[PDB]
Amino acid sequence: DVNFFDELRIGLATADDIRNWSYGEVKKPETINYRTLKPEKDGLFCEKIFGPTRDWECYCGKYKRVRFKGIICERCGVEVTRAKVRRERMGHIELAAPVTHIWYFKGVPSRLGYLLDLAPKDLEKIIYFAAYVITSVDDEMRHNELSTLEAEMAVEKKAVEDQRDADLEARAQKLEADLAELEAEGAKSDVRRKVRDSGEREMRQLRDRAQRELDRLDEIWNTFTKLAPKQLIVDEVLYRELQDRYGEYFTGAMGAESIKKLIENFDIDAEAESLREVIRSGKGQKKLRALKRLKVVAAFQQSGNSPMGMVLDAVPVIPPELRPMVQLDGGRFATSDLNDLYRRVINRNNRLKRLIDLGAPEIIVNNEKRMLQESVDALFDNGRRGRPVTGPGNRPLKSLSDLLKGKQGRFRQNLLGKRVDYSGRSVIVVGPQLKLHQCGLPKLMALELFKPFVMKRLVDLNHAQNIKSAKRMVERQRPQVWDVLEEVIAEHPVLLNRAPTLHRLGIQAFEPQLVEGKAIQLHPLVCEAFNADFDGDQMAVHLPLSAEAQAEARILMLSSNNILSPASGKPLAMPRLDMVTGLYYLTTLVEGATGEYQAATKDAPEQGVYSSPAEAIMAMDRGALSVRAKIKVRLTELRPPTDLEAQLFENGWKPGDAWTAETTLGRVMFNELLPKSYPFVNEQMHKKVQARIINDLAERFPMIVVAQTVDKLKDAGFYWATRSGVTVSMADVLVPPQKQEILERHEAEADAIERKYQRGALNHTERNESLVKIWQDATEEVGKALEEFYPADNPIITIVKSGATSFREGLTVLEYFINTHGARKGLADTALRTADSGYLTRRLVDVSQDVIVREHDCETERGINVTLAERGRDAHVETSAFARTLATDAVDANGNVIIERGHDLGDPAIDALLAAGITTVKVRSVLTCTSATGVCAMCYGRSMATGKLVDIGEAVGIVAAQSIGEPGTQLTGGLPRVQELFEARVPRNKAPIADVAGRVRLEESDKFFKITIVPDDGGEEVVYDKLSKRQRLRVIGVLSDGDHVEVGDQLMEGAADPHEVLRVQGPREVQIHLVKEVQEVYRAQGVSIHDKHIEVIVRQMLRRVTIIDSTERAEFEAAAGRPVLMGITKASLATDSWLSAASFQETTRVLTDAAINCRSDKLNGLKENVIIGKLIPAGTGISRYRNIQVQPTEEARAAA
Ligand SMILES: [Zn+2]
Ligand SMILES: [Zn+2]
């Protein structure tokens, strides 16, 4: 129980291993006495083997006190020790007949079948007693006696011929007499042919019966001469006759013991060398059939596992506590299915001993071994072969396989996902008055959550005298604890989470504030992250305990420290909904306002000017100044625009200096919210403006400044959202009466046009275009009739303009029916959007979880170019160029270098680059990182969450998977296309790529399109004859006849085979393609994902190569292999960790292949450490971080 083990290894458990594990053989299929209800002896639950029921108490009771431990009672045979051993100790069952392990027999491909060259359909007939197998053969005796055996065989065969020919002549000669009697008697011409037909056919019968015996004889002899071990004799009768004679020359048997023998005399090395034949043709599958099988044969040779392990002589019995039998509440009993499966095994096994001792016939005995064989199969993997064993109600019993795996089973999530103490949940309610780092916690919830803490505090304080006195003091909720509760809660962070958890921001830390009520008060800014509606949504609370946990919450998972989306870098805590309209109304400029500014007239000065913002406030309180007026005022503690100030100053930005600009009091009150160092804005604030502003100020200020600035915007937005006058009513919605009238107007144009179409004015496409012109003219006419009819400041329009976000006439009966037909498809289609996105996100995580930053820099010059603008700004520079690092300097044509290599490439850098007009830039990428382990900080680049360089410990693979899986809910060219890419499957509709460079010859044929490429070598022409016209052409105009094509261009519309572009353009260009297509899907849905996230996933596909002649890349540096592209699922299953891969998909094959290979897991990944409870090798788990030493400086200790 050290908690730090290096490796974890498997292997075939031999009969001895099982016997060594067990604490005694369970001999009876009994559980507990129906009266005493105590465990029966020698049976399941037997305390004499598994363990005592009570601590330090034997079965009889002659030893009861803890005084004696480690001894065994000489009466009941029970060891006096803790009752827990009942959960650690196993038993075993000695089988009267060997049995095959179903995992190596029925497990496809048959591990045993591949190990002995027995087809699974043939092997199934052997171990289940459906055919005999030749175990041994005496070659010398069969050869020395072949002469006499052949003679005796020919003689016996001849005696059959002499009988046959003698019989036919007796039938034909007798038929001649019967027919001769017909001439003397009345001759019926019909009967004459009827008798002959009867006689002739009878001869054929007599002659064919003889032939069949001859063939049976020939069959007997041929099989005996060619008789070789591993041959199967399914004929039984043949086998018996093959045993009556020649029985002393060979041997044969059925069942697992026969398979046990074939494995006995089996030279593993000899069978391998004959399989080492890389010659003997091999281009055909015949060698692959040996190639595929050689893996299973070599695995046993390279390891020490004896292949005998595939046949069990003893079966281990799982401890009772894992298969418990307890009496349910209400008097009823409950017990696991394993007990009924073990019972079937131990019953049939015992009956076999009985039959063996009774000298029963082999039909009965063999029938028992077959029954025993099936009982062990059911015990291990019930249902894997034949119908599963079902109990009352016809439900399949849960075997050990099912118990191991399952979605809710102990393999996938029952082991990974477990319930935790110090937790709780409740419905959430808005907490508009909360600080971003705070959360409303119901007093009762915070009480029970911190119960141990408050118990100690109110005991330290002489309120309660002992612990027990403190417990009741909290349970009864005596009013004296509350004051103690706010202390224990102070500066003690708690974790909030809302299911489902999509990204890491779905869990954040908060300062707990005791709040009246039973609900949880959530800050209104984190809703975006949690995606938390306030329509009854619930959230969970977890209480970090250890000092490390609290440190991780305060530092890593603090709410205020996580503002930017770790997927796009954009801000999530940005104001939204009311806060937007509130600020939109606050800063909007209304012409002709109440206190509007007026230029000095002939006899009066300017009346819109005000001394300070305070004066404007006083003027606002009176009916003088409107918040949205165009007044001009002087400012002393605010910052003027960068461009305007330079004129007014240059000596320095105003710290207390005065300056006058014309704005609105709102815009003044707004800028007061921003930092004092931030220049003035003077604009009506939209989501984007506030989004544009929050970003800009997030780069130039620490997040604490951004955290407080977003909080201040929340208050203002909410405050002015109320004074905004935004309310809905009939006059706000209603209907533009011109619409219904004008709609009936244009409808007449479409009906009479059809009238004109029928007569002869159709003119083909004239109708389709005309009807479209009318429909779009009316559709465009209603927009104006509605947009111009709605006031500019209409509440519906205001909400739309700010960016926070027709049944008005009513529908008749039939109209509403049609609407339901489509509305129900959206709800059902939405059900499939969430399932697959979570199934994709799991595979994504399954393949990239072990990817973490391991070093600051790998120092590789390799990089990837970026298109970066094309106007002569690109539309997607924010996803691929932003937050990158330059592998090479940015050189201008004029010789001036701007932005040096290894720079952060901030948006100001993008503009500085755009200033010099540089189209492309080479950039570091995880696709090119040469890090031996994971990736490096520089290659990865800026962390989207922190805005700075990525920290060394960051586990970017998981963040990438979440960044990709989360938006999967918004996929419609959607989720299937994405899985098509990440899984590396050939495209749904394949598309060709240019295999070389040169011109193109477009040929038009009704059957198919033909694209020939004339190389510029010029060498052999490349023909792409097979082409479906339904696939269209690729766009540049369209690819026409005679155009030039490059080495990687796509010829027709569709998806190019990634495996195709791999061998053509190489690995690096494949990864650029996959990221290109993947990002294009999400971009189609308006989803902003930084390329690096996709790149992290793509990096893991090209990490291995195929070995054509004697896998990862690092092994080759210390025998030719080609770069390989493979899907995430296949790649994940190829991980070095076997229990990690076992938890992923199909645990049986991984477990069987792992046990045979005898693999050892070094616990390198983080999934493994999660299962066993070790510190994951990421974040605070890295060695460099967890081995830090904290010693106070000698100078500080002096101060004391
Ligand atoms: Zn005893
Ligand atoms: Zn690197």
Image (tube, rainbow, N blue to C red):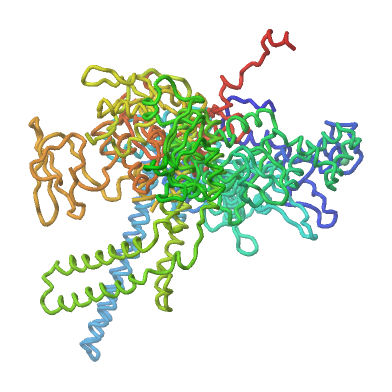
**Quick check: 511 above or below 43?**
above
Residue 404 rendering spot, x and y as whole percentages: 59, 45
Which percent across, then down, holds residue 298? 43, 30
Q: Position of residue 371 (x, y in %)?
A: 59, 54
- Residue at 32% in and 59% down: 161
Name the foreground residue: 203 vs 552. Answer: 552
Query: Could one spot residue 999 in this view of the protein?
Result: yes
Image quarter hosting the C terminus: top right
The quarter holding residue 1195 reads top right
All told, the count of numbered labels is 0
Task: Give above or below for 499 relative to 282.
Answer: below
Q: Quadrant of residue 1108?
A: top left
Left or right of 173 on screen, residue 1176: right
**Residue at the limit of the structure toward the bottom, as seen here:** 186
Q: Nearer the viewer, residue 195 or 609?
A: 609
User: Which quarter is ligand 2 in?
Assistant: top left
Query: Could you say which is closer to the camera, residue 823 or residue 443?
Result: 443
**Image height of 218 relative to 139, above or below:** below
The answer to whether residue 355 of the structure is visible from this angle is no
105 or 168: nearer the viewer: 105
Q: Which quarter of the picture shows residue 289?
A: top left
Tell whether 1193 sits left or right of 271.
Answer: right
Horizontal and vertical percent position of residue 1174: 62, 30
**The N terminus sits in image quarter:** top right
